Image (cartoon, rainbow over all chains, first blue to last red; front, side):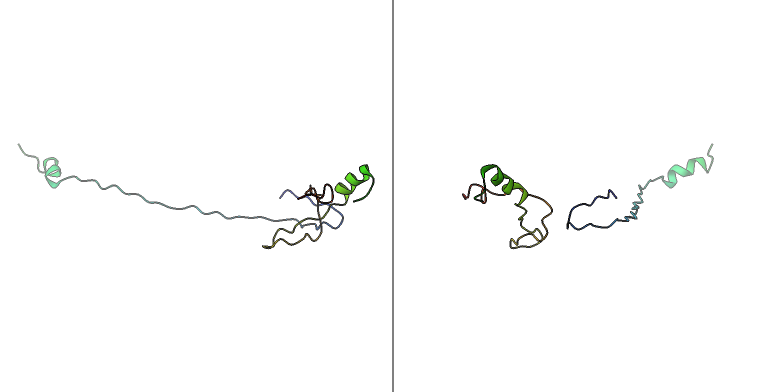
Length: 48
Length: 48
């Protein structure tokens, strides 16, 4: 802390220790995605 | 403040340590000074 005090009778506020823990915040996203079984059939049945 | 004219302005500065306390809702007078504020023309020109 930037410390300063002074004066003749002006009260001197003592030194200050500041520790702040500041958290993070999660936001898990998701897009859905579609592949049909008719799409996967042609790789995996091997027609003529 | 019937001092001589250059002591009147030094009465207006050195001895106008008469402020309004801050934390109170109704205006209360200051407790321990900490500054010579620029007064109103009271104690200098005596006009509202």
